Length: 317
Image (cartoon, rainbow, N blue to C red; front, side, top):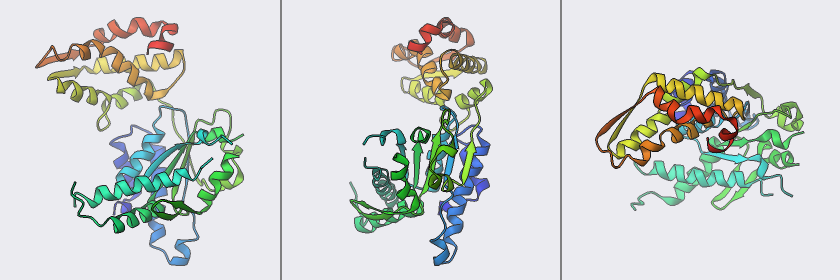
């Protein structure tokens, strides 16, 4: 019964994991809220309305996949992510639905437990996941601007509502929430087939990330990037401390290197962190119960000479 969450609560839940993107959090929340409102209606009306599918528009590294993935995680919905550019060949587009039933049974069994010890009725469990997927599932179709200007026609019956054959039974894709995402640098949403345009009533244009947005992505969300390296090096009994001046120095370098070559967004932070933490990671076992403080000087000693050379950056970080 996490479907009863009001939109304001979902925006608060999604703030614990995703920095900014307030505009994208509302439109994601009112799509879920419509699924709740649909169930409180009469049977002839509950079945003839269509979900408020979302069309996300923005570059990479802005966190439009986390907004959708965490969205299903908090409401307890089955989530799947498919790359639309894998279907361009000649295609079993319905595999995106059978994979949703495959992830729904694992979610239902996971919550059937905690409530090698199978004391749960597998039949009723599978038949609940079969219903949870078709009444609450979420399919994230990534890179959908690359099937626009053949593949959209096969995605259509899934959004239009069809009954797809799965190993556990038949599921109905009428009330599944669909999210399309892409950069739309060459094609526009108006270049999608008209049937797809009408079936994406909610559309959001996500914002770009500034150099001051990385320092939040780096420190703020629940289990951020540097929080991971703290707990990882804490396995080797090494306490790591990042001075705020050094976190800001990593954000200034990632944003700067995202400018010289090509912009990948917050994904740049992964290669930046591991590169600077290389000496610490290699020598961590032979350094027990130590306390290491990361200063901006130590950051520039390992990155500033590399981040200045553009030709080196395209390869090593």
